[PDB]
Every structure is written in structure tokens, then in C-alpha cells.
Image (spheres, protein in one colour):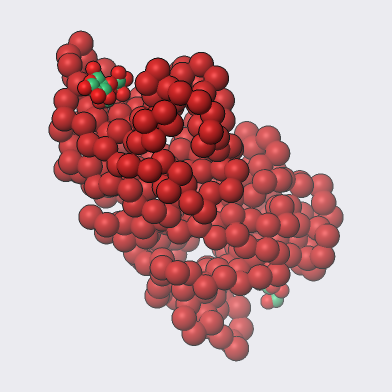
Length: 160
Length: 160
Ligand SMILES: OC[C@H]1O[C@@H](O[C@H]2[C@H](O)[C@@H](O)[C@H](O)O[C@@H]2CO)[C@H](O)[C@@H](O)[C@H]1O
Ligand SMILES: OC[C@H]1O[C@@H](O[C@H]2[C@H](O)[C@@H](O)[C@H](O)O[C@@H]2CO)[C@H](O)[C@@H](O)[C@H]1O
């Protein structure tokens, strides 16, 4: 009955602490003011968007790899190996209908994460780790990111 | 479990039909790529954002008046008079923290409409009329709109 909107500007390489955590029912949307589908190779990730728990766990890791022409979704506890990674083939195909900008949305359905690029749902991710999101990061491979140097993030919390 | 994201480009003077209706629990966000808090007088509204029913009723009317330095929230059935209008004083005060752009968010709480400008909740509107929103309009007074000529709209439906 009293939802909230929080806006963040995330510079590449940075991690921001959410003024309000993202839990079941809440939403996170990343806005990119540019799209470079022919930027270069990632080491191996050109661009990575992360949702992190209060103790460093990678609730959700989203990685775009041009050289491999794929998108990877994984998770992992702090100082622990990477877990079972789901992948979606064809990067450009997902950004069809972009036009110099893109938005990635993540719905926290509680027991899963729905990832949408623009208007297309790309995957229904099954949570390998549970918990509320308290911080988000935008990591890039030097000079080869498919997104703008600064990505805007909007969270809609306190829905359910 | 299968929420949806729809993007719309709304030119001043137009109405768009939502590919997906907005009902209780859903969200609508308007994005303006400009802010003119010194554009001029509205006749009387400099800019109006409307949420309309499949019947033409104005579920929610949001109007910004610079000459009257106020924001009006009303509703009305088709070919009927305007109802009880709620008002918020001080236009600029609501956009504090903007900086060349703004976003207005409307949460459909079922029996109310929470309106947020950027991160500030401006009013918890009590629905004078109920129903699902099926179309949206952006009206303005020639040359005196406080928003860009084109406003982007993003709806998040199928939440509840
Ligand atoms: O799980 C995402 C994670 O992948 C790492 O690379 C993996 C690679 O994708 C996989 O095919 C191989 O078997 O193991 C590599 C190392 O775990 C990236 O290095 C890391 O940054 C994440 O993107
Ligand atoms: O209710 C919104 C509606 O207001 C109309 O103007 C009002 C005016 O603000 C009020 O002071 C007067 O008593 O009644 C008018 C309605 O006849 C606008 O003309 C209309 O466009 C809406 O903005």
C-alpha cells in the first residue's frame, strides 16, 4: 500500500548499496543509453550485471559474451565456486527492436527470477540461492561493454 | 509467475492502446527526457497524463499547471462532469532532484493510485472510479509542456 521507487546511477566497475532491498514481488530494471553488439571480446564477460545478498553471495549473475555470442545466468556463495549455469544463445536476437538503447528487467518471483530484455522474456531462472538483494554491480571488460559506461537502475519495492 | 514488460512512445496529443491492461498490482511509469519548470501558462493544464478505461472514463487524470503552480488529480466518466479533484501544491518542489529529466510512476493498488515523482510519493489517490486501464494519453498546451514532446511509458503487468 506504500511501495517505493529508488533510482541509482551505476558506473561500470561499481557496486551500489540499495537504499531498499529487493525481495519476492519486487522489481529491478537496468537502463542502458547505448547498445554495442560489435564492441569486442569479453574476458570472457563483455558486460555483467549482478544482484548480491547481504553477505556477498551472487544471487543472480547476468553475463553477456559477444565472442561466445551467448548470455549466462549463474549464482554462487562468497569465496565458493560458480554453480550450475544456464545459458541463452544469440545475443543480438534478444535486443531486436532496441535502437541505440536497452533495458533489462528482473522480477523476483520469490523462488525464481524472470529476466526480460526490453519486452522479451529471455529466461525463467530457478534460484540456486535465496534471499533479499541488497546491492547491485555492473562489471565490464575494459572498453568492450555492450552498455553505456553508466547504467541507470530503478527498483520497485514493497509490492507484495 | 509470467509478468510482462511493454514499452510505449507517446507523442504529445496522442492516446495509445495498451497491449496489456493495467489492473490492481500493476505499474505504469512515464519517462520524460526534459523538464521545463518555466515553460509558461497552461490552458489551464501545461501537461496532462491520463489513465483511461475501455469505456473512455478518466480513471486517473494528472495535470500540471505552472501558472497556478499546482498538480491536479481527478477522474470522470465519459461525457460527464469532472469529479472531486485532489490537489498538491508546489510543482518544482516535487521535481527536486531531477536535473533535466523526470519520471512519474503510478501503482495500481486496486482501491487506490499511488503517484510517485522520481522517488517522492506525492499522493495516495482514492479511486473515484474503478476498472482496468486500457489506454493512456499525454495532452499538453501548445508549446508549454513541462515534459519532452515524446514521453516513454513502461508498464509492468501480471504481478499479482
Ligand atoms: O558462471 C558464470 C561465470 O563463468 C566463468 O567462466 C566459466 C565458463 O563459463 C565455463 O564454461 C567454464 O567451465 O568455467 C569457467 C570458470 O568458472 C567466468 O569466468 C565468470 O566470470 C562468470 O561469468
Ligand atoms: O479536474 C481536472 C480538470 O480541471 C478543469 O478545470 C477545473 C478548474 O481547475 C477548477 O478550478 C474549476 O472549478 O472547474 C474546472 C472544471 O470545469 C480542466 O479544465 C480540465 O482540463 C481538468 O484539468
